[PDB]
Length: 235
Ligand SMILES: CC(=O)N[C@@H]1[C@@H](O)[C@H](O)[C@@H](CO)O[C@@H]1O
Ligand SMILES: CC(=O)N[C@@H]1[C@@H](O)[C@H](O)[C@@H](CO)O[C@@H]1O
Ligand SMILES: CC(=O)N[C@@H]1[C@@H](O)[C@H](O)[C@@H](CO)O[C@@H]1O
Ligand SMILES: CC(=O)N[C@@H]1[C@@H](O)[C@H](O)[C@@H](CO)O[C@@H]1O
Ligand SMILES: CC(=O)N[C@@H]1[C@@H](O)[C@H](O)[C@@H](CO)O[C@@H]1O
Image (cartoon, rainbow, N blue to C red):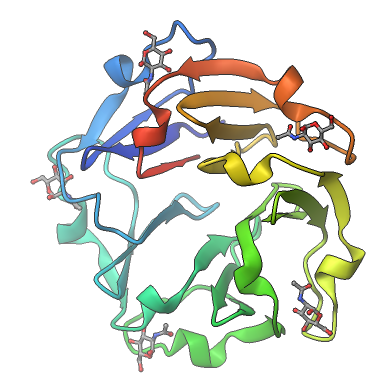
């Protein structure tokens, strides 16, 4: 059930709405304002597959159901689940089953998310990757459980590492040979459609399946202008 709404932070404000389906749709003019300010200094701001919003701010991490209207004081009701060290991460993201993945100091870690202030998450997390993980530009999951990654200007996908003895990049399938480093945002919707913002323009299409598929030549243009101004843009 339910396709998730697109969300984004633009000029310190938080908006939500169904994603735009053509370049004549002025998304910002119709989107619901779900936060009046305070959103631009989060380092990370993302949603779990269970619908909980996670935010990293000033080295601490907070969670709560997302705000539904502009006067919902999200940070006043969010639960603080981390008191320090959350700005050390380069990436912080969920797999489809609710496990949190994190890249810190070139290593990849995985575990169920912290549920309280006193939980030393980084200490109990499993190290599933020992080196190479700060070299990616993007690292994100498809809803089918495959890990997608942009390395240099190349694009790859493969089931995630089973342990730190698993050399992921060596067995990954290459699904793109160039141009992937020029995107500002690159992410999946909840039904597996790939969405990307490249120089102000917003595109969507089924993801490439092999290195010679010219994704940008076939993708649908769903937005022209303003998308490079967002600080966060995600489903
Ligand atoms: C980061 C955060 O929770 N910001 C909210 C803001 O969006 C909302 O408009 C306001 C309502 O009083 O409370 C907070 O400031
Ligand atoms: C990144 C990480 O796991 N930081 C945790 C922090 O959230 C927590 O409050 C503390 C409790 O001892 O341990 C850690 O440092
Ligand atoms: C990016 C990548 O695939 N890194 C892996 C690393 O996680 C793993 O510990 C090692 C095993 O020899 O191989 C690679 O370096
Ligand atoms: C961003 C993008 O779509 N890059 C693709 C690239 O992956 C592919 O190898 C090439 C083949 O023609 O076309 C494009 O450039
Ligand atoms: C961020 C945003 O909503 N940008 C839209 C843009 O995609 C669209 O092409 C244009 C149509 O007039 O309006 C806006 O600028």
